[PDB]
Figure 1: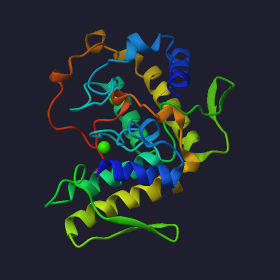
Figure 2: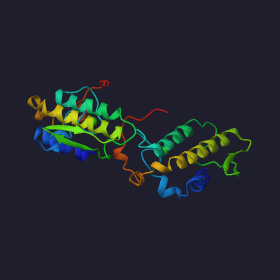
Figure 3: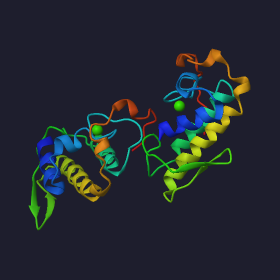
Length: 122
Length: 122
Ligand SMILES: [Ca+2]
Ligand SMILES: [Ca+2]
């Protein structure tokens, strides 16, 4: 669920997820088109593609089971669709942390008109 | 950066870049489709293809290092991506100057639906 995803981004980056990531670049908001603007945005692009692959449950609005073991996020439960969603979210929140070095504030509420037409393929 | 591209265009063609070039043909505007209508538009098509080949930086918002040396634009800096962007802009500035003799005012704000369906490849 969206709020579990937000918990993981806050924990992994220290950044409050909504102003810092919900509108970043060409892919971090609802939708997405064009070419990813930088690595953070490319994290959002892989996360969008990861969600498109989920058949069987709602990626944005169902809850999954995860817990924190020794500094890392562990996706569990016995529903394979929900755990698949959890793995998308975990992967994106780690990717955000690893690309915190190139994070540009100029891309934080990026104008959708600046995103190319030619959308990158997954 | 876009503004640096515009300065090179004014200096090479003497025309004020937006009015004369920002909407020309099927490729000088944002996006582009169809085939190039003439040689100025093909300058724009090569420049769109040039920006598509750039990753690592942002063609529109990053400012690169360049200078004039004896009536020639010279791209420098030690960041290879940005110099590529500079090189893409310099070539189109020169290409618009070299094709001012077929610049058709009829293509100045050319309706994009008039552009053919099968886009040319880079
Ligand atoms: Ca998105
Ligand atoms: Ca164009």
